[PDB]
Amino acid sequence: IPAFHPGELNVYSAPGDVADVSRALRLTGRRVMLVPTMGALHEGHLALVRAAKRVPGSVVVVSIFVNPMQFGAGGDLDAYPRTPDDDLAQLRAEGVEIAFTPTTAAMYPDGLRTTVQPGPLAAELEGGPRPTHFAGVLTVVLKLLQIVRPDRVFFGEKDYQQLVLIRQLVADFNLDVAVVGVPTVREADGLAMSSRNRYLDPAQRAAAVALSAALTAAAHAATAGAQAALDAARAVLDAAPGVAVDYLELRDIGLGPMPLNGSGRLLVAARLGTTRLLDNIAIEIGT
Amino acid sequence: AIPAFHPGELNVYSAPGDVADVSRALRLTGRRVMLVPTMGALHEGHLALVRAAKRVPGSVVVVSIFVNPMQFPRTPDDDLAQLRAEGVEIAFTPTTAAMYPDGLRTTVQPGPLAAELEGGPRPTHFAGVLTVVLKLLQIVRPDRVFFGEKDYQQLVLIRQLVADFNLDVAVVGVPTVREADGLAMSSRNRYLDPAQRAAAVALSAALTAAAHAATAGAQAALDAARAVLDAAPGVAVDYLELRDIGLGPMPLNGSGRLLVAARLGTTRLLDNIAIEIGT
Ligand SMILES: COc1ccc2[nH]c(C(=O)NS(C)(=O)=O)cc2c1
Ligand SMILES: COc1ccc2[nH]c(C(=O)NS(C)(=O)=O)cc2c1
Image (cartoon, rainbow over all chains, first blue to last red; front, top):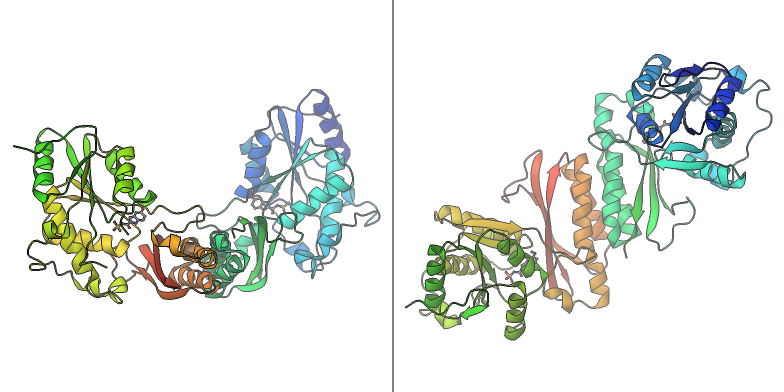
């Protein structure tokens, strides 16, 4: 064990440091809560923290790591916002006791060797054009789950496909951890929190509202069925200035089929200039 | 003498004079007279008007029942059982002759809004509605009168009636009562076969979707509504219009009202909803 000063933010770099300290708190009967982030924290992140925080006797581990494996190449990796400064101050403000900030060398000392192969879900939606994206995410998440060994792990529903693949990872490998999805934190107009938002000029920031509006429209249109919930989304996206829709898709909650159903999930991906915005909502199909 | 009035029971008057003497006698005893005008065939929409009128401290409730033959289907004993079961104390149920003893002589001519929307098919309908509501107001002299939001063009015309003629009555508009799938209640609903009944869901769906799309602005809202109407078979949309809440031209942002009207077979349906543009 290295130092753990309780009630204070404790920052570890080494997997073995966070692992030892984690394992120690797990005996003293505290409950290890893990919030995996790529940093550049926003209110969405803090909701995850706060939800972690509200677990009786929780000790909250925020991991901060920009996983080069879920990226390209790609274009993604050198772009991704990096502000450990703010990130760590926000965590201190929130009363988070551990930040785990590993080096790429310490996570990947053997490069990409043993990895997680996701199911067929991972080739769809966001995995369509990014076929190794989810393998990266799941490999890093498994490794964090192994290093920290939490009781519970907290993700947003912003990345809803990731959250399902994570529930799969956890079921398929018999991981002893509860996955907590946390409803998406939204701007005042409805724009889903994202680090990727900073890269929207005013004009785009204003057109961006169209995603949350289309989806909230379809969830109310849905009493009249799937076609009308879809047509209602599409109509709003259409009415909106330089939103180019990648996809708009209605699925079941586990991102399978989508029956004549009630409960489903509506997912949109769109570009505003160069900025790719994702969003999704619970939909109950009415007729 | 004042007509017999038994507190706590449903006292029915057909005579305009009788109900006038009762309400004026009641106003002086410290009751606040609330009017709920209806055309009978009472549904949950009416009982919600009633419940709103009931909850005013010291309210006495007058529910008029009167089929206007001047504005554009009888169940007298059941209607009265529903009122009794709401704890209404007055039902006013005039004949045509009692209300129009001289036929149609003096009438209310509405302003130009009576000519729009629902006044397109029926050009004289709101003349008839304003004439009987003005007369109901002078007979009963209520402190407050309660109308559903269902017929929103009508409610706006009533508020204009009241302002224009310096009527000293509060107009209260009560949010539309809907079925479980959101179909605005109406007595026409029971005429729809299962196919039409199912397609009819699309008026409310349209309007709710519009109201949520509205954060993306006025055009998104309309396009949302229309997309949902376009997904329904056998729904012939007579209009779909967004207006300010007084039914003038929709202003660039801020509060508004989305209205629709449609034919499903022989049955003409309407609905409307609050809109906040940029919300
Ligand atoms: C609770 O609501 C929200 C809203 C937006 C969110 N974005 C992210 C995120 O980017 N996570 S990561 C692991 O850094 O890629 C989480 C999240 C949660
Ligand atoms: C409170 O919600 C509602 C919903 C539907 C309604 N319809 C009527 C109605 O038909 N009134 S009438 C024929 O002019 O007497 C009132 C009403 C109220």
